[PDB]
Amino acid sequence: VLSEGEWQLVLHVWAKVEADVAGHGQDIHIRLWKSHPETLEKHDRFKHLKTEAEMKASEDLKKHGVTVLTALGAILKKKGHHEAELKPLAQSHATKHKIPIKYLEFISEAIIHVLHSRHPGDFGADAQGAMNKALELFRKDIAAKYKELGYQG
Ligand code: HEM
Image 1: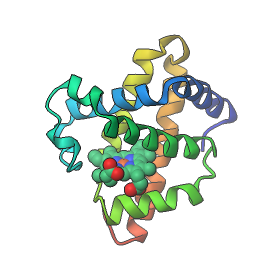
Image 2: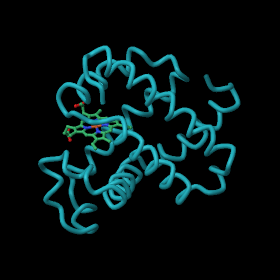
Image 3: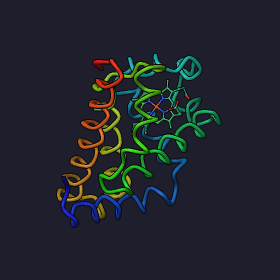
Image 4: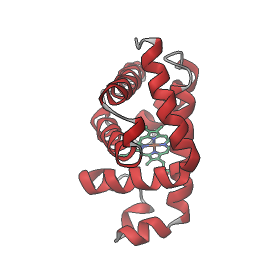
């Protein structure tokens, strides 16, 4: 569990994300796919995007990033009290999309990279550690739900 101070650092940087959710979501996807191209294979639509400029020009991808960050933001704002929000996400990611926990590690890395790239003055070592803990809690709780659903992930 995170301390109150750690949650405040998480939500402080999250407020910066909320100034441009769409742009952050695009950058996170592009960073994830560049670092781990196998993840781009899970999007039947997005996997045919060939260049960074094509990725930025995709309204579908931009909309998807807002959907992703809206879901993650709603979870983070619960400060760990997120079972109701997390359960449907685990259901779809385990049973329909088949997303292994390691891919959630990859997107967590991309999130931290983009947040530090855009907001270094609000995302130093302490805030990075807090965000790392919050995303680790998210992944640990998702992994438990995966197992409950019969998916080892
Ligand atoms: C922070 C982690 C993530 C969050 C909050 C998140 C959230 C979402 C949401 C809200 C949706 C739409 C509703 C649904 O189907 O559940 C979605 C769909 C989907 N997600 Fe994720 N997701 C995450 C990570 C990933 C990763 C790492 C992958 C693949 C490597 C992935 C693959 C997909 C796919 C294939 C879909 C359905 C196709 C689409 O709607 O674009 N997700 N995700």
